[PDB]
Amino acid sequence: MGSSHHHHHHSSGLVPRGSHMASDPNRIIATYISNRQDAPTGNPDNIFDNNASTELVYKNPNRIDVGTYVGVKYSNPITLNNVEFLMGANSNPNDTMQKAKIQYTVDGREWIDLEEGVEYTMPGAIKVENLDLKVRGVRLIATEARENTWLGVRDINVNKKEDS
Image (cartoon, rainbow, N blue to C red; front, side, top):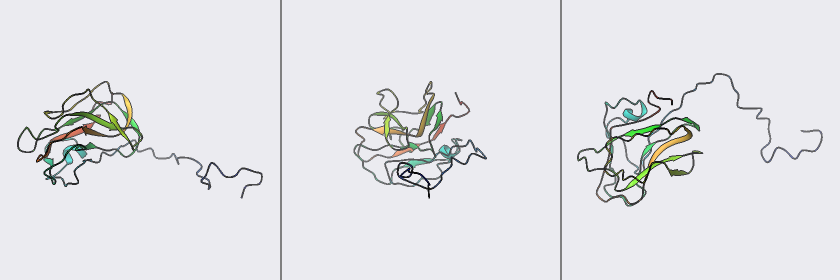
């Protein structure tokens, strides 16, 4: 129980030792995010697998003002090279953001601006480059969504055979 003074390490005690370090998987998962608590129309695999063969569209709530956004979160802070949300609309190509840029969380907590002040209200295929920066998850950020609207998704992947 500690010989000399110490008052434990900061707060928590025990002997964490380290981060284990043994069988480095080097694999990061990508969970789909969405301001709309809905279920994937068919299969979000287009994102989880990055194939763009299955369908995916959020809509449950046919009305949302500000905050409406989606993308894909990771498992932990990694070294990203470039993300690209390749999505459009479910039925009508005019079904997506109202006006906004893309987002991304750094410490897997807060989410800050990502792409230029573009209006991802008419985005067909989202993709960015020269984004070599560690990041946590990925997602778009709306500033004034529209009512009676859905979210058509085709395929979104991070580091799709890029890693640079």
